[PDB]
Length: 304
Length: 304
Ligand SMILES: OC[C@H]1CN(Cc2ccccc2)CCO1
Ligand SMILES: OC[C@H]1CN(Cc2ccccc2)CCO1
Image 1 (spheres, chains in turn red, yellow):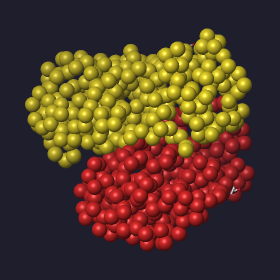
Image 2 (image 1 turned 90 degrees about the horizontal axis):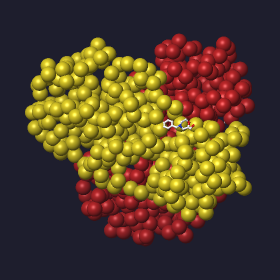
Image 3 (image 1 turned 135 degrees about the vertical axis):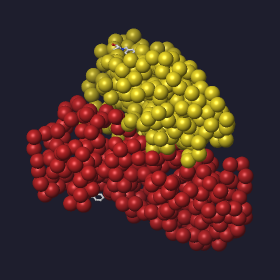
């Protein structure tokens, strides 16, 4: 019993982290097979960052300008290319610790673990969600760029995120491993405002199921509702709309607890309208939205 | 910027986890050099667990009764001994992935990462505190016993916890790596009640400092207090007493933010007395006590 915000074991990703230096900028790279992936802004002076022309900046750069260090050994760069907002540095040595991996672009609401790194060295691991506004609420200091987000299915690391940017509001923006930003953000030091940070409704419902499973039941009410009625209340409270897709995904949690999804929706509705009245659920005073239904099933079933 | 509940990178500990089977009981072992450490209750039938005599149960056990598997390879057990509530199984092979390590007994309030394992396989990592009542609020299903708690100082893993028990209240109890329980708990399926789960005051103060550092300042008040006045309020709210030792440990956070410790104490006092009035601090609706001052400095400074 018990329910924790839990990251994937990070060992398989620790084995992939390298330091990338271009001139006076150092940040993190991901070393998979004989390619090192890093944010293209590695080539920028924080002066360049105001209005960078990356193609023009790149002309000035050779393989030998990219310094790649894995532990305290230097990798030989034998090629470099730009793909969207990432550089791929071809190195002469395949990473001997390359795990099975995929690059996936996740959807808003999906959770992943971040291995926070400085100078190619891991400092910590935490669990995130891609916010509905395509930001993440990370913990990232200068030098943390190229830190990656990932899921693990058994022995396969799915890389979903690379850290690029802190917005003036101190929330975070980055790319998939093809170098495409999540949301409308660009790798430029300019005014970039995030949209509404709404709550991931399907994730809240999953975590209410996790609470019931773990004995926290005080909030279960006598009511039910409809998707349309619930969605009216959701919108009023900056909750994302619940679809029949979300209801389907919650099916297994509904099955295990015998609480119909629409009943749990009506319980959520009363919590929104009545508040927590100073009570907690799974040791939280607010409704947690950084567990997916898959996450709740995984942790409640003990998947390795 | 940003502040996350962050575990240590778990790779160094993933490399230490093995499966231990005695008869029909399987749980986790820690393989360091040529010794595998596991909970002694591995030798119990859940029938034995009601009133086990471990010394008498152990007489019935030989080296060959302990089945140790690291990946899908079996280790040869060439010796076994009981030390307090753990078994040490001597194996014929030194773990080639043994990191530099120490066994430390932590104090209540100290934080550590848990690598949750089933069948010797890692499922997740999360950050804990040893509660003032010597319990932890973990996430542990059947098969998770022998999962360990640890801190990392650069390249040295300090093992502080091994999981043994869930109390009837669904909180967790375990040992240091010498097999000595934290708190008054025993490895027996009997009524064992925890004491008061009080808040770790020094940790709350550290996390209020982390909030200020990260731009959350709405709660900073115009007041100060004394250790004695603050402690009167602390006791009333099931907060642990603050000592001059705690004030000293917060010195660096006081220095960086220019907020005297006793001023931050008076801010905490008003939050206890007035509540959060529906506001959040670092995205929490309650006062977080699972970051130490050391943790706040580490994460706010980017230690690897
Ligand atoms: O009123 C309805 C809710 C959901 N929101 C949709 C939304 C979708 C994507 C990203 C941000 C926001 C708007 C604001 O509040
Ligand atoms: O009234 C004072 C506070 C602190 N408590 C001390 C305490 C110390 C250790 C373990 C549990 C509890 C008692 C209860 O509330």
